[PDB]
Image (cartoon, rainbow over all chains, first blue to last red; front, side):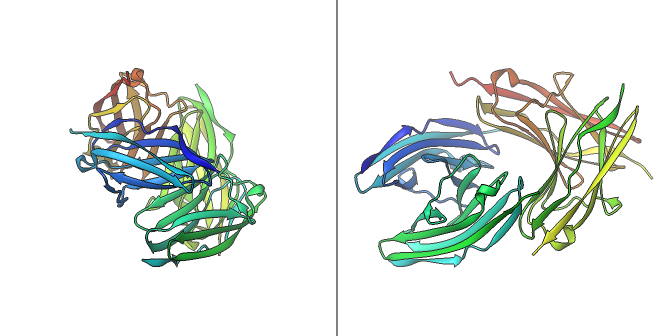
Length: 97
Length: 97
Length: 96
Length: 99
């Protein structure tokens, strides 16, 4: 039994509107923690252009394609299991033109 | 609060070695269920070419690129929340050249 | 100048309907040759769920997603430059 | 029986952060369908391991540059040619340093 711990935290990013952007984390824990994603403190809605990818043992990626100005904001991830919780956030800046 | 429930089950799949294969499910639930994937009864090991994608509201896909014969087997997914659990499975046959 | 040559030829393929399939080739030549693709002797119908990919190391790929039974058939690629031309083909079988 | 190539959607200036991907998208027509040459700053484009050109339908082409480096900054040009003539357009890519 091991509390969830980030091995790789979210990092701030910027992209141009219409382009794609990727955020990435690695989070470990026994049992494998479940994740909750938020934007500006509200539950993240994936919609048509956002996807969450799970690879490897602890690797998760948040991918946005066809980014829009509205996608600008603070993205938070929270990992939880029976032993504890841990959370981090980063900012996405979608630039105009 | 409602028990998790597949709106689209895993379906049996087949591909040629070196090609890609995709399993797709759709599971709803309030609260949104957490998923657990298994291969032949053991916890699924996401290798280098295996990824799990979450899209939309309840869309989940298991993607395997560049399949190898080792990927042959029974894949199971369990969706759990505070109201209960649901599970389904299907078979993947990677055919050699 | 140099005649186009297939460093990797098309190989026969099979896929289940609704899944994806990829045909890969490697073509060299100076000048870099232009490619023309056919299916069953007629120009390849470039529509949804079909894409032609070009990447480094002379790599070219024909990718088809969400295959339908109509996608079964013989796919041919012809490479041509000023020094000549070369062609090869392979079969795709869509299965249920 | 011929028709000079014409851009229906042109390359657009782009910007991305080092390490992210950037995409350029065009639509070009013409009879017979034109062949394309891609250039970076007047030189033929070398795709390396990180660039792929995707052709969909008859007119759509996308230039995907992944794992961008600041040295990728420059002017990218595409030229479409058939037996009836040629047409060309270019855009600028700025790969901003992570710092």
